[PDB]
Each structure stands twice: as C-alpha cells, then as structure tokens.
Amino acid sequence: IFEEAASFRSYQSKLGRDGRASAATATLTTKIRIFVPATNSPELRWELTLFALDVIRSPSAAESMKVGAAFTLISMYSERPGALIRSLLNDPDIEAVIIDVGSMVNGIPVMERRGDKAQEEMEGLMRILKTARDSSKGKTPFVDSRAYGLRITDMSTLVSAVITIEAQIWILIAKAVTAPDTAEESETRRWAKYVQQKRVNPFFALTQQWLTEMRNLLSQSLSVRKFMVEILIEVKKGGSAKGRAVEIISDIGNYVEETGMAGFFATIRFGLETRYPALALNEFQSDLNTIKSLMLLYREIGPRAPYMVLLEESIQTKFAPGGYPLLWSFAMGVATTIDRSMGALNINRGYLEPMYFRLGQKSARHHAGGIDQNMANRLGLSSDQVAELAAAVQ
Amino acid sequence: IFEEAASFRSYQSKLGRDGRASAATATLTTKIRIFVPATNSPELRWELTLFALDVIRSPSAAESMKVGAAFTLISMYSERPGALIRSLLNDPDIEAVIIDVGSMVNGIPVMERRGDKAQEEMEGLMRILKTARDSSKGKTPFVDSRAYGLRITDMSTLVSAVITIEAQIWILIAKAVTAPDTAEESETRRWAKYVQQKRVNPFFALTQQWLTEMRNLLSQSLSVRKFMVEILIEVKKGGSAKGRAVEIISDIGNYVEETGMAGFFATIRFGLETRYPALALNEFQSDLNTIKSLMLLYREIGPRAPYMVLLEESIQTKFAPGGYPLLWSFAMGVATTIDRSMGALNINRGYLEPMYFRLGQKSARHHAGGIDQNMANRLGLSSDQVAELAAAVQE
Amino acid sequence: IFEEAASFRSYQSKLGRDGRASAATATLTTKIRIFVPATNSPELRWELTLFALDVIRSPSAAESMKVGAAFTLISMYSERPGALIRSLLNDPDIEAVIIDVGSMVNGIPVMERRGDKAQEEMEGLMRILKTARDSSKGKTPFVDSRAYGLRITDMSTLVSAVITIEAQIWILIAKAVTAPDTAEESETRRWAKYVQQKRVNPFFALTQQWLTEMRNLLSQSLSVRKFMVEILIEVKKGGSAKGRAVEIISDIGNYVEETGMAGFFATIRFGLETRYPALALNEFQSDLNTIKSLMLLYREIGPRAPYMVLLEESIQTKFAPGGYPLLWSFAMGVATTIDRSMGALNINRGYLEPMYFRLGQKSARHHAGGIDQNMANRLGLSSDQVAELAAAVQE
RNA sequence: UUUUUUUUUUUUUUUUUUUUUUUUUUUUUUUUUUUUUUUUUUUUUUUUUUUUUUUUUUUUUUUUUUUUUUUUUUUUUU
C-alpha cells in the first residue's frame, strides 16, 4: 500500500547513483608548483614556511601559486611531505608538480632545481615576496615581528613554530566555506583554547590580516579544501599512534565535521529526537520519510559525509532543508527556544513555514518543556512530580 | 519511526574511526636524551637523582634535556630503568637516545661513556647544574638541605628516598594538565596521606619551587605525560603482587583517573543516575541519546579512556559538556546543590543554559532532594517518613 | 536509558584490571636476612626468640634487620620455619635470605653457619643487643624479668612461651596500620581473652615499651604486614585439623579482617541493610550503584579483600567512603545513633555531608527510634503496640 | 457494434555551538559464664425371640339447538 511509495522515495534517492561516470567527463587539469622541503634541515623548513606565508601575503601572486604555497605550508609535519602530497592529493582539477627545494640555496625565494631554465621565475617569486612586504605596509605575518626575523636550528623550536602556524590554518577551514567572514569570533575562541592548553606557542600568532588572506584563499580554492579534507579523514582513522602534530589537526576536525549542514542535523536533534507530540501530524510524514532516506543516504556516502560542504559535493543539495521544510521550520522553532547557540544561527530562508516554527516554539515553551508529555515510563514518576517540574520550568 | 535517529547518531560517532591511519601522516621526531642507571648501585642512583632534580631546577636546560631527565627521574623504581622507558615509550613525537651511565665518573655532572662529542655536552650539563644552584639562590630541591648532601650507600634509604621524590612527581600529574595552579592544595593533601600512612619518608620533601618547575614541565610536555599514562595504565592492570613503589603509583592513579572530564561524569552522577522527574522533559532526550553514545564510545576507547585529557586525544572534544549542555546545566544544578565538594569546580562556560541549571537546583533543593519521587518500591516507605525527610533536609 | 549508565559505572570500575603487568615495572628488591631454627631444640628456640625480641628492642638495629627479626620471631610455631617463610613470603619489595642457624653457641648473638664472613656481623649483633638492654633502663622485654632469665629445655614450656609472645605480636596487627596509637585498650582486651581462656602463659607478658617498639615496626614496614596477612589467609582456610598455635592466630585474624575499612562495611551494615525510608531518595542512587559496584569488586578481589588496608593495595582507595559520601554520612548518622561502640570511631572526614548525617540520626532516632516504618510484613502484628514500645524505649 | 477525459507551469546553497578547572588514606565494637533423670493412670460387670391388621360389595347408552331475509352511484366549494 504505502510501503510501495516509501520504497519508491528510497528508489528516487538512490537512483542512478550506482556505477561509474564515463572518462569523457574528465575535466581540464591545472598545473600548480609545490615546493616541498624534502629534507630534515630545520633551517630550510622554516625559511620555506616564511616563503609560503609570504606567497599568501602577496596580492601580485596568482591563485595557482597560492594554492601551491598552502600545500607547502600545511604538510611541514612529515619526514617526506612528497609522499603525503602524492598519496592524499586526489584531485582531477589539479596536476601538481612537486619540486624538492633540496639545499634551499636561494636567499629569500626557493632555489630552482633547474636554475638555468628560467631566471624570470626566481624574479617573479622575488617580486611576489617584495610585494608581500610592501603591500602589507612592512607588517610581518606574525603579531610579533621577531618571529619573522628569528631562524631556527633546533627541532623542538621548529615544530613548536610549524604546529602553531598549521593550527592557525586549520582553525580557518571550519568556517572558510560556510561563513567565509564573521567567523573571527569562533576562530579566536579556538585559538584561546589551543594556547591555554599549551599545544601552540603564541609567539607565532598570525595577524588578522594574514589569517584573512589565507581564509579567503581557502573559501575560493576547492583544491586546497579537498586536500585538507583528505588529510583530515586520514588522521581521523582510529587506533593509530599519534604525534602532537596530527592530534591537533584531528582535534580541529571536531569543529570541521558537519560544517555547513546545520539545517540537517538540527532537524535530527531538535525535530526527531526531541519527539514532541507534533510528530504525529500527517503533514510531517513525507518529511520524516525524507529524513530516513537522507540518513540512509548519509550512510551510503560513508567517510566523506561529514565534510560534504567543504568538498562542495552535489549531494548536499538533497540534504538541504528545502527538502523537508515543514519539519525543519518546526525543528528550528524548537532549537531557537532550547539552545542559546541555536538562537544565533541564521534562519532567513524562503521556505520557512512560520506556523510550524511557532508550533516548534509552542512545543518547547508553551508545553512547559513538554513536561506533561513524558516520553518514557522507565522513571515511573508521579503525575504530581511531573506537574512540579512544569511549575519549576515556569 | 525514532529508531533510525538513534542508530544514525551511533553511525556519526563511529564513522571513519575504523581502519588504520596512513603512514604518510608520520610527524618529525625530536631527539630526547635519557640518562639511565646501568646498575644497582645506591651511590649512582642517588647522585643521578640529584643531577636530574637539578636539570629541572635549571633555567638554562633545554626542554629536550628536561623531559628526558624527568623520564629518568620517574624510572628510578625499576630493576631495569632502561627497559621501563624503552618498553613503554610508544611515542611518534620522539626518538629516544639512551645513555646507560656506567659509573657516574664526572661527579656532580652526569657522565658520558665515550665523552661528550666535543666535550661541550659535559660543559652544558655543568652550566645547567650551576645555573640551577645560582638561580635557586643556594636553596636545595628539598626542604632540608641535608637530603642534598646525603650520598646514600644503602638500598633501604635509597628506595625510601626515591619512592618519596617519585610520589612527589606523581601527586602533580592529577592536576598538571587540568588546573596547573590551585594544584598545591590537592598535592599537599595527598602528601599528608602518604606520610601519615608512613609510605614515604618526609625527610625527602621537595620545595614548592622545585615542585612547580616539575609541574610546569608536565603541563607543557605531552611526551612526559605519554610516559606517565603508559606506566599508570601498566601498573593499574591486575593479576600480580606489587612492590610498594608501583603500589604508590597505582594509589595516586585513583586521583589521576577521570581528570579533565569533570563535566562528563558529573552529568552521569548528578543528571542521569539520580533519575529526577525532570528527565521526562522532551529536550533532554537529545542529550540522553548523546550521553548513551558517549558511554558506548568510552567503552570503545577502552584502557586510555580515563586519561584522555592527559594524553591529548582528539576524542576528548566529543566528551566535552558543550556536546550535551542542557543535561549538563541541569546536572551541575543538582551537583552544586547536593555535594558540598562541588561548586569549587568552575562552571563558568558559555552553554550554561541557566533555566535548566535552576531546574537542577529546584530538583535537589526545591523538590527537597526530589523527596516525593521514590524510584523503587522495595522499602514502600510511608508518606509521613518522606515528609520528615523533607523537613530534615532544610530544602 | 539507565541500565546502560549502571553498566557503565561497572565498566569504569573494572576497566583495565585484567591481563598481567609487564616485568619492565619490576621494583628494586631490598635484601634481608631471616634467622630461623634448624631443629627442634628448645634451648636454641627460646634463646633465638630472646635475641629476636632484643633486636626489635634495639635503638641501633637497621629496619632490614628488624623486619628479618620479626620473621625469625613469628615463624617459631612450625617444625620447618624456613619452609613457612619461603613458601608464604610473596613480595617483590624484598629479597629474603634464610639462615638455618644451627646450635646458638656464639653467646647472645645468633649462630653463623659458616662463621663470621665479614668478621664483624657478630659484633654488630653484640652492639645491637647491648644497646637494646642499655637503652631500656635495665628492663627486660617481659613484665617479669625471670621470663628473660629462664632457659627452656622442654617443648611444652617452649610452646607455652612462644605462643604467648607470638600472640602478643598478632594482637597488634589489628590496629598497627589503622590507628597505630591508642591501640592499647584493644590490646588489653584481646589479652583478657587468652589469659582467661588459658591459651597463653601470662608469665610471658611483654611490657608496653616492647609492644610499642614492635607496633612501630609493623606500622612502618609493609613487607612484614604482607607476610603476616599471607599466613593469616593461609590458616583461615578450613578442611584441616589445626594446632593450638594456628588457632590463636586465626582467632586474632577475626580482629584483623575488615580493618581500616570501617566506613565501607558501616555503609552496608547501617543504612543499606537497615532499609530506612531515606534510602528511596533520588540523592542516594549514585552511591547505591557505587556500593553495588564495590561489593562485586570486593568479590572479584577475593581472599585478600578483608586485608586490603594492611597490604595497602591501591584498590582500597576505591573503597574509601569519599566514593559514596552522601550514603556514608547518612549511614554514620544511623550507626552512631544505634551502636554504643560507634562514635568512638573518628568520623571527622572532609566529606562529612552533615545534613545527611542528621537525617541518619533523624531516621534511626527521630523517626520513633527507627520505628516510623517496619521493613517487611514478616508476621503482621498490630502497629499500635509496637509504637507504644518505641515510645517507652524513647529512641 | 461504436460514441468522456488524458503535455506543461512551485520549491530545492551556506551562516549557531564545541579544551580545562571540585572531591577522593586511617581511626569503633567483636572469648566465657543458665538450664536440661525419674515419679500418675490404664481387666471385667447392662440390655438385645415372639405376639396387630391385611378378599369383595357404588355409579357408568341416549334424548336440545343449528338456511335465509338490510344497507351499499351521484350532486358543495374552489
């Protein structure tokens, strides 16, 4: 009867998603140069970090080389970052040319391995680096200029630096796609955390200007977000040995997961699992069947599922609350009454049903925390006790 | 209808945890020197402990020296201190170099077997130890300076001494990463117990100056907390008799467990297992579902679970009460009302949701301990007795 | 919901607590000499006991000597005292070397089987036993000096003597680690019995000065308490005929069991098995779950459980009433109101929770002398008569 | 056998939150003690065959009455 319809909803949501796309769909690659350190000499690693910071500080650089810089800038972690790149790159938009900087002989720019083939590229980079200084009005990437000056001999001091700047990139990714500005509040809150717990050395704190230039690069290159989410899934995998370096990335991950999918998970939290009497309304049944199909769909996607928005994967559309707007309007009605932080999520969408939102508000507030409507009999609480709870709840 | 939601919560929590993370993630190892007692000689072991105390007392020693000094200083228990470190190291931050010191030939500075590579390491150690003495204005690590000169010749007094300095490190770890100041109250209260029980010899008590220099090394190095929690799990394990040495560590452990997860367990104690009538309120169902997922998650993590804050594991975030703030605010509302130990824990966090906290307080205070709502009927207590309890509780 | 939380409490309690600790944890042994009788000669055995009493009486003897002397002393019961020590010693703190002394010809010091190997040991012993005598203002260990004077040549008087002295050690162990001073009342009781019941010859009573020197040795050595509790568990096992000696010990052991865990058992004995109306309150639920977990934990620990304070096993901490203070404060409020022997136990802990203690009084006294309910309808007599009895009893 | 109708048209990105912070050894009591053989009754005994009455007898066909018989189209108003 209805079972056919429910199975048909399921059918639509999985239809044609099976199998493999034709190689005729293969997109034009773009060629990007990544200067990998490829050495354990701490001097070259820190100089390359400064070079890379400056590439992103520069308004005269192209996006193609800025992405390449972000690929050198994160990934200072491993003994062989060329393995990290080649194994986790996984992007058809990109062909990355990896250059070992080797001895890093050149003073402020990277040394070219084919020094002779073009001097103009070394000039281009030097112009970019000068532009980085001059356009930033002499202000270093760091809030203390001495951090720009000092060059590092000792591996403890190197990693203290590197992990602190990496962490400063990774705090960005959490909101770079989903609220590309206005997220300095959240990012400084997370910064406060990592320095309080002494994981990062705040001598290497980066200026809001540099962080914004990098956050913008992240908002507008998918290629670098793809690499970030690749490595973030990689280190999320359990039971491994962890160094402090990957641990802080993983930690950051917990802010990066479910990003840009607020609507979806908020209908599960403050719609489904809150389980007010309103879930018996006939109107919602289509929406409930939708969310069932979405949860199974989420499961079908597997490990990439919590990051779909950063990856800009198409399937997100299905996830959007336009697919279940009665239940979503209701759920936000609950969310905004229950959770003070849900008050501050923007719910200006065209498909807001204000009567169902007000029913959401009424289910939490007007029903007195739903206190009359105890969900389960395990407490075996007195009727009197429930009434007292409702009185205390105002 | 609802089952799919809870099973999806499960899914989210277990997603991508599976499998083993690629070697391409492997971090730059730093070099740590650990000086090790080669032999059961009391003269060696006590001088080396004094040296090691002085390395952490030093303003001029490098963190790479200091953490390896702290490793030797808390390996002094073992019949084979080199084996203890190398077997429980388990740290990709670190490459350890051991210097099994054969005969302590240099005297005040530690020896090195083939010499320092250009003599400079011995000179480095000497500078370290001088600067320790000079910066400390002559004052020893110990509260009685006679301990510093003592140059022990018998194993009985050595183990008395060692165990007492070790205990003094281990009293720190309980707060070193969770409130590294305000710690002195706890650390002295624990000190009181071990001396009252005559387990440690108070002749060897260490100065607040030295203890804070070591507490800071613990706060700022994960590599030493990794070693500590490795050995703390190791000795917590059953099915052997114990030497007083590992027993005292195990004893300390009971203060180190649950550290830095106050909020989590407090929601279990004073939200969940107290089973107030307030758990019928619809909103808390989301949070209850979360804590169920967290309990099963805790189980899934296994032996490291009680120490996840000291070992700085990402999963901790999951556990933070920001993840279930309605239940947490209510549970702290109960906790602070019921337990006169509570409320000395800081609950100034953004997600306090104080209507639910006040409902917590109004359960335990206003509902007279929730007096009416008896959970189980095996006593079948009279209404008059419940009223007497309401009177005596002072609401 | 709640079932998972209760299982989680259990999980926390048992998490780790399996497998084997790695031998990399293995503690430094301390090497100790135990002199033992080789043979069934009373002339040896009594003089060796006098020597051992004097070693413990000495101001100049080392702790390593003293513990070894306490081993010499308590092993006299058996036909193979070497076998008794070696087989029931179970301790990594220590490394026991046994000397089967042979004929005690070399004066007041014990015999050396291969002569003096340092050519100093006998002189060490001479100094020890001289300083024992001299430090004492000319006293003997015994209240009558003739006991010190009289050599023994028959087994019957030997065993009369030995048992009397061994008993005097064993009466101590019941409060050597808990309340190690103010023990004396419960060492003069405990000497009432035995003398009255004619199990000991009070000719061999020991002076308070010797008993406190031995009590101190017991408080401040774990290794001796470990040996005592090993043999105390050994003799507690049934299914065998016994000698007089072991019976006196076993009888003692009924004093030694549950020592130092007053608070734990008192929460079960008072409060919990009293099943007051107050136990139905929401407040206790955490604590009740705790006690349940502890009872099954007690079961899991098995034979050593009643002695975990004297063995100072880490787990003890778990048991401490800080782990369930609301239930405990109430339980002590019951216990002190009901039992005339309670209250003379010191309950000045920090986690006193006095509103619950006052409710513990107000149940067992204020609620009609603990007659505001009757727990179950075991016979179904009339309420009024029982209430009249409670009024006449006046709480 | 036959005789309708049967294209389409909306909506469908995102935006919050998320490290910590207290407690947490121990303390009391804990042998015993009284009673604890027996003692009386304890066969029997009365009464218990039978006896009266106990066929039958009245009445008991029938008889009156019992076809039918009148009435029975209409008419005002709107």
Image: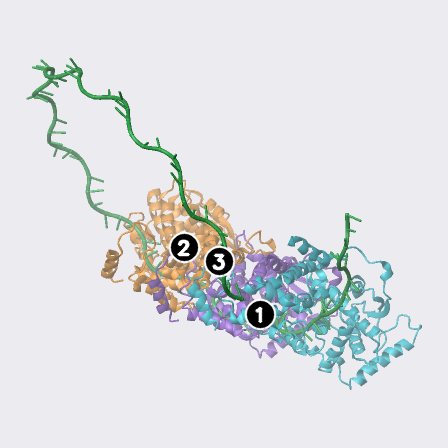
Chain colours: A cyan, B purple, C orange, D green
Are the numbered discs 2 and 3 placed on the same chain, yes or no?
no
Residue B332: x percent and y percent?
50, 70
Residue A367: x percent and y percent?
51, 69
Q: Residues within 10 Å of mark 3 (few under 14, many from 20)?
A: few
Amino acid type, callout 3? Arg
- Name the chain under label 1: A
Q: Are marks 2 and 3 in contact (CB under 8 Å)?
A: no
Using residue C125 as the reference point, say whether residue A33 is left or right of it: right
Nearest the eye: A364 or C39:
A364
Distance from disc 2 to disc 3, alpha carbons, whole Å, reads 38 Å
Q: Residues within 10 Å of mark 1 (few under 14, many from 20)?
A: many
Amino acid type, callout 2? Glu
- The residue where tag 3 is placed is A378
Residue at the limit of the structure toward the right, as seen here? A117
Identify the residue shown where x is 91% and y is 77%.
A120
Residue A45: x percent and y percent?
78, 72
Nearest the eye: A268 or A42:
A268
Q: Are marks 1 and 3 in contact (CB under 8 Å)?
A: no
Q: Earlier in the sequence, mark 1 or mark 3?
A: 1
In this orientation, does residue C362 appear?
yes
- The residue where tag 2 is placed is C258
Amino acid type, callout 1? Gly
Using residue B311 as the reference point, say whether residue B379 is left or right of it: left
Q: In the rendered structure, find residue C230 and report the number of the disc placed on it.
A: none
Label 3's element? loop
Identify the residue shown where x is 45% and y is 71%.
A391
Image quadrant where residue C265 sits: bottom left
Tell me if residue A145 comes above or below residue B191 in the rendering: below
In this orientation, does residue C131 appear?
no
Using residue C192 as the reference point, say whether residue A392 is left or right of it: right
Q: In the rendered structure, find residue A360 and report the number of the disc placed on it.
A: 1
